[PDB]
Length: 103
Length: 294
Ligand code: HEC
Ligand code: HEC
Image 1 (cartoon, rainbow over the protein chains, first blue to last red):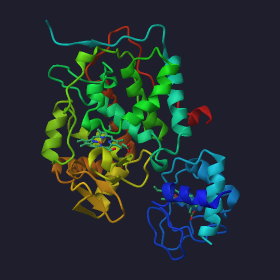
Image 2 (cartoon, chains in turn blue, yellow; image 1 turned 90 degrees about the vertical axis):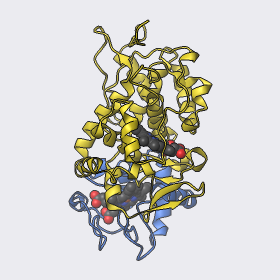
Image 3 (spheres, rainbow over the protein chains, first blue to last red; image 1 turned 45 degrees about the vertical axis):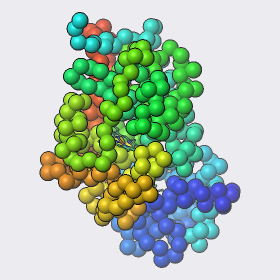
C-alpha cells in the first residue's frame, strides 16, 4: 500500500486521538508506538476498557485491518468512537503507513 | 382566514419500503463519499441542513419549518446563516433525481435522520407527507440563532420552536458532529474528537476539558481547549447556566438517556408545524446499512 496516502488517512482520521512517535503522549486513545506485535490493552499509563483487554490479541496487519473495518464489531464495548475504514485500499494504505510510523 | 395549517400528505402510492430505498441511497452515498471535508464525510452537514430547514419555524403563526421545502429557493438558499449547506444540498441532488416523487422537505429532513443513524446515533422515527410550497412562502432571513450569545438568549430563542430546557440541551448534543469553518460562519475548528460518530462527547468535553475564550482569525471569540477542540459561546453557556448544567451532567453520565431524548427532540424539530391526519401511516424507523449486512 501507499505509506504516504496512509499518512494522510492517519492525519485526518486518527491523529486527533492517537500519536505515533515513541514516548508520545496519551490522548483520547493510547499512544500507538510498538502497537504491532503487542497485546491489546497494554500501553503503559493508559486506561483501557476491559473489553479491549479481554479481547487479548497480538496486533498484526490482518487483525488490524478487521478492527479498523468496524471497531465495535471486532471489540464490542470498545470506547474508540470510530466509524470504520470501509475501503480495503485505505486499510492497506493506513496499515502500511502505521507499520513504519510506529516502529 | 384562519391560522396557516400544514396537513401531511403521503406521496401518491409511496410507502415505507419506498422511503427505505431513499434512505439507502443517502446512506450509501454517505459511506462512499468519505473524502469530503478532510474525511469528515457529509454526515454532519446533512444533520445541520435538516436542523436549519426546520429551525425557521415560528410557533406563533406557523411560518417557516420543514414542510414547504422552501430551502430550494434562493432567498433561503443564500441566507448567511445557511452558508455551507450548499454542499448538503448538492449531495442530495443526485438522490432527488433518482426519486423525483419525494418532496423537497421530506428529502432534507430524511437526510438528517439518515446521517444521525448511519453515524451510529439513536434510531429516529420519521414521518413523510411534507409538500412543496410556493416561493413566496419562504421565510425571511434571520430566523436562525446567532453563536455569539449567552444562555438567556438560547433559552429565549428556543421558546419560538417550542423547545424546553431538556430538549435544548439534547439538541445541542448534535455539536458532537463536524466542525466550524471560517469562510462559513466566522468560526474555525472541530467541536470534538469523533467528528462523524454520534456520541455524548459534547457533554463530556464541556465538563472535562480545559477551555479558554480567545479570538480567532475572524476576530470572533470562541472557546478553545488545549486538546484542540472549539465551542461556540452559545455552546459553552450550557455550563454557565445552572438549569442547563444539571441536564449537561445528566447526559454526560448517561448516553442512553441522551440518545432517547435527542431522538424525541430531533423528530419534534423536523415535525414542527406539521399536522398529521388520522389516515397517516405510523412513523418509520429505517434499517441502517449495518443491519442490512453492509
Ligand atoms: C477517538 C475519537 C479515536 C479515533 C478517531 C480513533 N481512535 Fe483508536 N482508540 C481510541 C480509544 C479511546 C481506544 C481504546 C478503546 C478501548 O476500549 O479501550 C482506541 C484503541 C485503538 C487501538 C488498540 C490499542 C490497544 O489495544 O492497545 C488501535 C490499534 C487504534 N485505536 C488505532 C486507531 C486507528 C488506526 C484509527 C484511525 C484510522 C483510530 N484508532 C481512530 C480512540 C480513537
Ligand atoms: C440538531 C442539530 C443542531 C442544532 C440544534 C444546532 N446545531 Fe449548530 N451545527 C450542527 C452540525 C451537525 C454542525 C457541523 C456541520 C459541519 O460540520 O459541516 C453545526 C455547525 C454550526 C456552525 C458552523 C457552521 C460552519 O460550517 O461553519 C454554527 C455557527 C452553528 N452550528 C451554530 C449553532 C447555534 C448558535 C445553535 C443553537 C443556539 C446551533 N448551531 C444548534 C447541528 C446543530
